[PDB]
Image 1 (cartoon, one colour):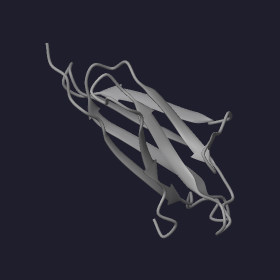
Image 2 (cartoon, rainbow, N blue to C red; image 1 turned 90 degrees about the vertical axis):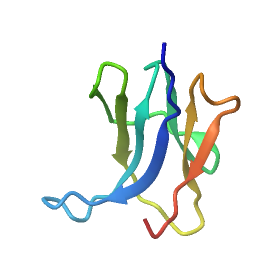
Image 3 (spheres, one colour; image 1 turned 120 degrees about the vertical axis):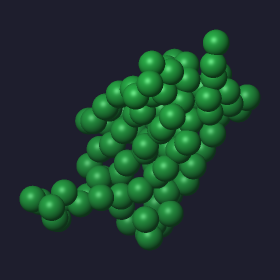
Image 4 (cartoon, rainbow, N blue to C red; image 1 turned 45 degrees about the horizontal axis):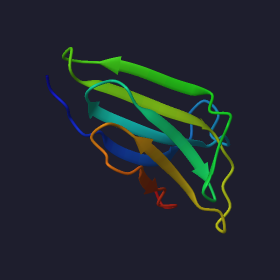
Length: 100
């Protein structure tokens, strides 16, 4: 058996074909086993509609998840990604740095 803690990066992107739109991304990488729970949060509350969830693997024991959706942030709002995984004794919350 092998288990590996996910790395978690939270960042924003504008698709080049539609630069006015903005997407909040949580990239959860290199984890095993594949069982996992991932949410985007706004002011600590789960965002129910997340329109993209793309899972892949490299080696049979390394998984990658890009979890992202359109958003329109204001400076007073806090966004984050919350991950639960067997390697994590408590949920890991990674805040979105608004300059990223």
